[PDB]
Image (cartoon, coloured by chain):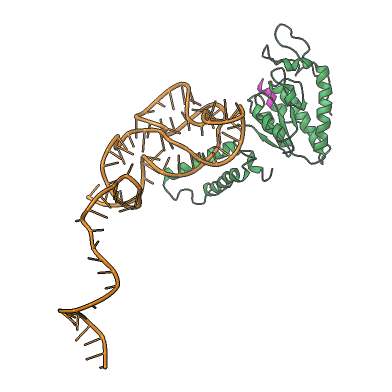
Chain colours: A green, B orange
Amino acid sequence: MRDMLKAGVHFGHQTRYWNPKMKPFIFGARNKVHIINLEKTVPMFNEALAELNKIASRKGKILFVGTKRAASEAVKDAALSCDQFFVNHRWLGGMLTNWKTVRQSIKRLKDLETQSQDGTFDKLTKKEALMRTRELEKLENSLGGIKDMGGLPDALFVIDADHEHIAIKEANNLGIPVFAIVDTNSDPDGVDFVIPGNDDAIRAVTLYLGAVAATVREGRSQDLASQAEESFVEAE
RNA sequence: GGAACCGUGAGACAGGUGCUGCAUGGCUGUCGUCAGCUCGUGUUGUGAAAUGUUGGGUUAAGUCCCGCAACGAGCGCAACCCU
């Protein structure tokens, strides 16, 4: 299970771009950063982790959102260790509301790939072929992780409430729990299960995203494994 | 006896570039070949509406690229015919 006393990674972040709604989580600004209370972060870890093991052992799906280039690679690897979905590139208009029509773009993607592998690849004009390549590119970029969705999630995990604020809104009107590791620059009231921690920093986001993923595989039907996201921490 | 056309007598009836196109169909002229004009759904607003068609680069052009709650689509453009 998780370990306490993480005063060598997370803690405070962001200079003076804070939101007054985050005072109950700030220790005390010193020369620059506001600094977060590691004493309050722990109790949050427990409450947030408790609700986690609930949906984990309940066979509930989670959607890890991460558009920020600070945890772009971490959000995927963490979502790979477990059988969960994720959004790494960019968050479309009516993916859940207008599911049917949106999937028609997925079917065309699979239909074009089957036509690009070898079957009738260079039969028609090249201009029309180059047209199928662009469509594939555009489709593969936006339909990268939503291609595995065949039915409408139980919860969403964000890395920053403000950056993925759009994901927070749609998750609120739908009545879906929201887990996320945000800091001073945000509104905690929007997160029913918030984790006061550094939003940025690769070594910061990987810790929890790796511990949370580890707590998911355990208490489900799998054994704990070493985090491969640590190799990406060498970005420093 | 009787089909046909035809002529006279008799009956029932036609016809009108006669008016109104501000009662109209159809067709045509014109601003225009001028270049853009809109829709479905989502989001924002009490609402009329807005967003998307704004912004940066670029082009003969919403031509294209980049960014962006927008995602797609239709008429137009382009392409498909002839000299």
Question: Is residue A182 at all visible to an observer of this figure?
Answer: yes
Task: Please state if B55 lies on the left or on the right of B2 as rendered.
Answer: right
Q: Is residue A153 magenta?
A: no
Q: Position of residue B59 (x, y in %)?
A: 36, 28
Task: Name the residue located 48 percent from the left edge and 48 percent from the top edge.
Answer: A121
The boundaries of the magenta stretch are A232-236
The residue drawn where x is 80% and y is 37% is A55
Q: Is residue B8 left or right of residue A107?
A: left
Asked if the magenta segment contains residue A233, the reply would be: yes
User: Residue A208: x percent and y percent?
Assistant: 76, 26
Please state which of residues A141 and A161 is positioned toward the viewer in this rendering. A161
Report the side of A81 relative to B51 (left or right).
right
Q: Is residue B44 above or below residue A127?
A: above
Image coordinates of residue A222 in percent, x first then y, are 81, 40
Q: Is residue A36 above or below residue B11?
A: above
- Work out whether residue A89 can be spotted: no
- The quarter of the rendered structure image containing the N terminus of chain A is top right
For this view, does A174 lie left or right of residue A128? right
Front position in the image: A229 or A109: A109
Q: Quadrant of residue A58?
A: top right
Residue A76, position as x, y percentages in the image: 68, 33
| Quarter occupied by residue A180 | top right
Quarter of the picture containing the C terminus of chain A is top right
Q: Main secondary structure of the magenta part?
A: helix
Nearest the viewer among A19 and B34 is B34
In the rendered image, the residue lying farthest to the top is: A31
- The quarter of the displayed image where residue A233 is located: top right
